Length: 164
RNA sequence: UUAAAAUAGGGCAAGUCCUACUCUCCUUUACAAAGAGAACAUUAUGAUAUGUAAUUGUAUGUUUGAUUGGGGCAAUACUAUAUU
Ligand SMILES: [Mg+2]
Ligand SMILES: [Mg+2]
Image: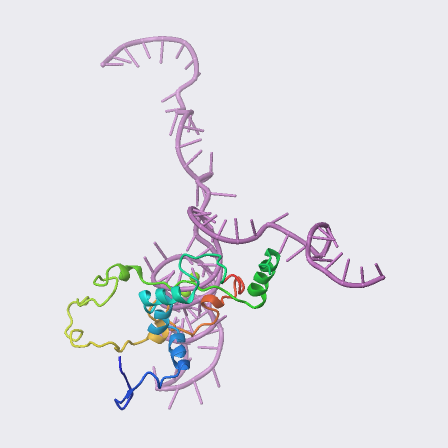
């Protein structure tokens, strides 16, 4: 809705330049980047794409020379894939146990107390608590946060760039 | 002699769809290595090290050829005797 600053004053949408909007949507691991990938407005984006293009069902149309040869398209595909390093987008994954049912134990937020026989656990709460020894033990499995390790995801060094 | 891309020449198992397998990429609770740290023994309750002590962890490797199975062989030969 209305964007409020630190002081609490409102900023109109005309004041925000488009470079900032592309910045928020470009920030990985955010809702804006996820909304761009999965569709910010499915009904609105479909009609927008349908109008800007030739048509939803129209194919190989002529507007009111010679087409590109197959030997050219093959050469253009090689120069795009192996020289310009242009790749296609991939999918984003989601927890299946939580996506199917949000109010189960696979999603988390269990209101039960697993530890029995203590009186301090019921008082200690909060989103961030104190855990002793995480620097040497970790959560278990994956412990580093994002953008910590090298050559992760599409930037793998096992199969090269074009393999992704 | 001049000018034209019609053919030859100048690289091409290609394009779309469906199915299946794999690679890649994510997850850790088990497999091997892990460069990080610990704890312990020894001299001191003050420092440098060596270990036969390491059962902790995070990136890395692997994780669908089961014949490494199943059969058969089963002391009391030979000549006789009795029993169920
Ligand atoms: Mg590990
Ligand atoms: Mg692994």
